[PDB]
Amino acid sequence: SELQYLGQIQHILRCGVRKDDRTGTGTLSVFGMQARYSLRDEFPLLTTKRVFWKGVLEELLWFIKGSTNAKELSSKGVKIWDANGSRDFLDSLGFSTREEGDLGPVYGFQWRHFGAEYRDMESDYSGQGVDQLQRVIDTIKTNPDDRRIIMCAWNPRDLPLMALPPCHALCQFYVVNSELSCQLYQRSGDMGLGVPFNIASYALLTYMIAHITGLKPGDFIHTLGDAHIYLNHIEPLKIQLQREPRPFPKLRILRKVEKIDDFKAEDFQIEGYNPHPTIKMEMAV
Amino acid sequence: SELQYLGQIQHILRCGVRKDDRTGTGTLSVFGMQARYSLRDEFPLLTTKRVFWKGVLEELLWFIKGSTNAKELSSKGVKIWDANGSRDFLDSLGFSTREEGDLGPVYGFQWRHFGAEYRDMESDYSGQGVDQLQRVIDTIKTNPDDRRIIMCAWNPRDLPLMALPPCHALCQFYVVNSELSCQLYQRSGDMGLGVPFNIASYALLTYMIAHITGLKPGDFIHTLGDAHIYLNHIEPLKIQLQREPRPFPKLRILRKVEKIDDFKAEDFQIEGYNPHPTIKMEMAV
Ligand SMILES: Nc1nc2[nH]cc(Cc3ccc(C(=O)N[C@H](CCC(=O)O)C(=O)O)cc3)c2c(=O)[nH]1
Ligand SMILES: Nc1nc2[nH]cc(Cc3ccc(C(=O)N[C@H](CCC(=O)O)C(=O)O)cc3)c2c(=O)[nH]1
Ligand SMILES: O=c1ccn([C@H]2C[C@H](O)[C@@H](COP(=O)(O)O)O2)c(=O)[nH]1
Ligand SMILES: O=c1ccn([C@H]2C[C@H](O)[C@@H](COP(=O)(O)O)O2)c(=O)[nH]1
């Protein structure tokens, strides 16, 4: 099922159109793609290249905790957001009053406190805003046939206060035959760098919510808007494209957890992940 | 026998020729030297300057483990390879898709998996390649008169993939009268920085292999190729030369260990190491 991501890479290289972007780099773009990754007895952690699974696990716990402080995640070993929370990148977009790591109201804030008035990254928002994450878990428990199980991060009101507007803007859940499925709408997909990271992130999120609600993981539908391949990624991706995929690993939950907040990093174990060598690709800031 | 190391320092300062180097810091070099350090009831840990014995002990266990991950050694307190595993140094040698601290197929990989195809620093290579380290131990036990007990780390095939090609490239063992001796051919010797470290390193390795095979440590012959003294080490070494050596310490193994992989850092104790104050010397890499 990894061939779907590879088939999207090969289709952008062969049929994608050249298109400029905000960064000083260049892209080959295709608008509108959809792939289905099965979560049943396998976890879609890519094997054609080693994916930062510790980054995937620590960033999601950072989202669930509602933290918007980049130093909070960077103190765990995952420095993927320090570029968007640095003084050089923040001061270029008019954000001159931030302390250290103030991305603004981003994925963590919108998941737990949607609509609340964002002060800074250290302020308390308990009881403020809409808790989309906990409301989604409550709806799955009480009314699984509901078609409104949605957690949205795209907030036009808080949009100008974010260092980078949300890429995974909207995700919806779906229950049938005790199988929890998840579809993510990604408005902008860095096919070389972020997309493998984002697929594993929301696949893990489905496993956590399926563990709490007592359901089995079903499918993860990855819907893309602007799916692009940066020009400085063509050679590293052509090397990844020649690699033969290996079977997906498995994700094991080591203890029964009742609440979404009680998940710790030690509760997860990836079993049987044998990927090809890492392929470091430059980020476009 | 420490007067031999001092005699090699004094000979390079008095008869060495000026010669440029890869780091561009300049050296005084002499090609072809040999010293014999007795391992009988004494350990060659230099006393004219404090040698990082924790680095010696942790790096050798890191070599025996076959690890080529610099972060694995740096997480133990030994940052001697972090300079060669940094992002800045990796991108200078064309390695732009490697992970931070992937030294490539270096001493650890060639000792345990010679000839195997190096993927990256997290891949499993169990059963792949030639296990030179276990093969020499097997030969010493069964055929001590063998003249081919050699462990080679210089691999021209894997050479362009190394952050730094092996300096202690080839070493040979030798058994007579139940005495295990070891000769090391070091192609490039930092007389100020690495040579004292390497003398203690392979002396420790000989003690470990002698403990397994039931032999007594004999001699350690330190054969050098390019023995050089960096220009920014002349004054620090001229101060070390005026210091009088103290008796070598002793190395005690606290428990009987059967296999070479079962050695832990807590199993070794240096008794009676009274060195002179440290002399910090800048690294050229
Ligand atoms: N042009 C661009 N800008 C971005 N800003 C923030 C992100 C999200 C992001 C940023 C960094 C990483 C990252 O460094 N990922 C790799 C593993 C990702 C993988 O294997 O897919 C790592 O940590 O080594 C991942 C996602 C991101 C992205 O994907 N592309
Ligand atoms: N020019 C140069 N480049 C190198 N790249 C890798 C090494 C191996 C190495 C690296 C660092 C040290 C080191 O820093 N050693 C000393 C301990 C020895 C001592 O104190 O005498 C320390 O930790 O300060 C030793 C060997 C090394 C070396 O010796 N010299
Ligand atoms: O989870 C994420 C976060 C970021 N990006 C990439 C997409 C873009 O290349 C870049 C953001 O720039 P815009 O699309 O906002 O201009 O980050 C992803 O692919 N996934
Ligand atoms: O165990 C080691 C590792 C490195 N070096 C030093 C020797 C050189 O001064 C420097 C770099 O090696 P060259 O590739 O320039 O030979 O590292 C040693 O002396 N011993």
Image: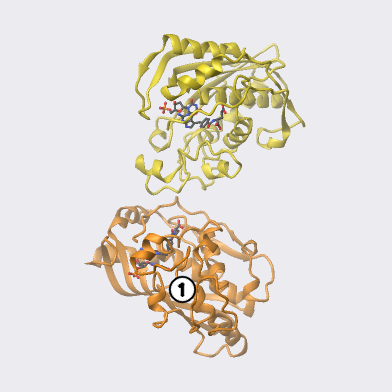
Chain colours: A orange, B yellow
| Residue positioned 50% across, 28% down in the render | B281
Using the image, determine if residue A13 lies above or below residue A173: above
| Residue positioned 66% across, 32% down in the render | B260
- Residue B187 appears anywhere in the view: no
What secondary structure is found at the residue carrying circle 1? Answer: loop
Report the front residue among A43 and A141. A141
Tell me the amino acid under the disc marked 1: Val
Report the front residue among A8 and B248. B248
Image coords of residue A13 (percent x, y): 27, 62
Image coords of residue A268 (percent x, y): 61, 63
Q: Total of numbered circles in the picture?
A: 1
Report the front residue among B262 and A197. A197
| Furthest residue toward right | B255
Disc 1 residue crowd, few under 14, some 14–19, many 20+, Cα 10 Å: many
| Furthest residue toward front | A97
Q: Which quadrant does ligand 1 occupy?
A: bottom left
Query: In this rendering, would A185 be left or right of B202?
Result: left
Hey, which quadrant is residue B261 in on the image? Answer: top right
| Residue positioned 46% across, 31% down in the render | B283
State which quarter of the image contains the N terminus of chain B: top right
Using the image, determine if residue A263 lies above or below residue B55: below
Image coords of residue A49 (percent x, y): 44, 55
Using the image, determine if residue B230 lies above or below residue B71: above
Using the image, determine if residue A166 lies above or below residue B209: below
- Residue A52 appears anywhere in the view: yes
Image coords of residue A265 (percent x, y): 61, 63
State which quarter of the image contains the C terminus of chain B: top left
The chain holding disc 1 is A
Report the front residue among A94 and B136. A94
